[PDB]
Length: 157
DNA sequence: AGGGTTAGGGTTTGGGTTAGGG
Ligand code: NA
Ligand code: NA
Ligand code: NA
Image (tube, rainbow, N blue to C red):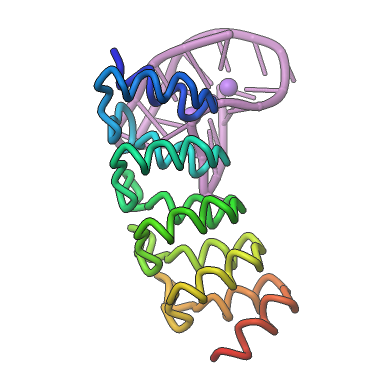
């Protein structure tokens, strides 16, 4: 039952137990529900060290869940800058589209994570990428009344 | 129970559309 144990340790932030389970042959890309992998759970929850351990053990940086979301989508939307940075330096697809049409930049924009927006752009995020409703991150900033984010994105339009 | 950038967390317990458990 090592997959179940790994998923739990990764979401719960038990880095020691993650390392032990990986040493015992746990599948780094194990999934029990909704295509959720340990890296995706750790990235959404904010567990940086576990993200680092899983990547070192070969975790698929671009694994997708039931909604087509990659770990970078979750880290970007849930405001985990350092995880966003580690994922990107390890090959995360900055322009990955989920099944809702969103890129990580769309999620960072929707949730007001300016530093993440800037890091994504630094790593090549498509500023003109449109979601399912044909909206760009800039459009989202205007809809949400985010003056600071609109200022960052206006400078790049 | 119910919602959800949902997969835990808010007294408390099992739903779901894919669909378990303090
Ligand atoms: Na629930
Ligand atoms: Na649930
Ligand atoms: Na609950």
